[PDB]
Length: 226
Length: 202
Image (cartoon, rainbow over all chains, first blue to last red; front, side):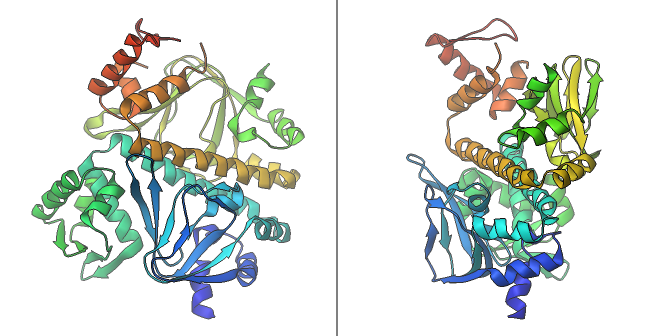
């Protein structure tokens, strides 16, 4: 249906790819839905399925023997996950759990081989997608090593707003729905450290802290801090 | 053998060996003096380098203008590799520790290289994924593993072949007040040895 296939076409994997080929793969894709709280996969599990959300929220968490788990990200419409599986079938690098009911469409490595075979020119476009992904994954590594807590709070707030923000009267209302601990986990620091940084941010007039939402009043200043 | 050194490149792991050689013969060789910057953070980038001899440090600009060292690389290492699939501004500086010799290609060569060997396209998507696989593996550990464990990781990774005091602790991620006390404990167990910018591993 138009809107659902509109949502799908927006995914990273299709960004800057041949529009006709994108249409082609979209109609070959299988739909799935999952209920609220459903587990899609567990970290460690073998996989060969890439998911593109068309509706609802999935969280990806990282785990450990000691130092249990850590929210990695939260994802919504047009986002994809599990993409590694279809390029390098192997074990899942995270967990994926449904925060709400979720509707998605999926593919596996075969559908991908067939796809490229049909539209060879897209291999170059998909390498660009795979590299853009890399650019981002190394960045989060660098930030975690070198940026300070306030800085990474600033980053995390901006990243959530890019993905889940509402333009509101010159500001951006971010409706993440996360505990203080989860924000800490995204930032990679302690509930306490992260909460101070937030408070200093409010005190500066850059943000207003309201329930489980953040109103970013001063993007420029907050960004410069990031 | 420059070819062999070049053949040990991550970009080439598990790709058609004839497709690999065809490109090697056709890559440009380049040389830089000691100290020279190859590229600066934020300049338009479009070139992959593979080191054939010498050492290159990669770093990002820090606040207060300070220095943030991301990695040291020697023969067979490649930097700028992402600019070749996804042009645009460089995300680090690459600076020559010694005199440097290296081979290069641009995205313009890479387009022609796939169009000549469509077999590779999939092998190249696998490479990137494997690298992607590796970086998260690094991220998990970083949020989880102890600085000693991460100083042990940096030590083992650089030891492939056998940086100041405030440069190793950048690689590792935490304080030099932590990285050093991690390093001393290792030496007390008799694992490694001081000597200056030099370390001996057992």
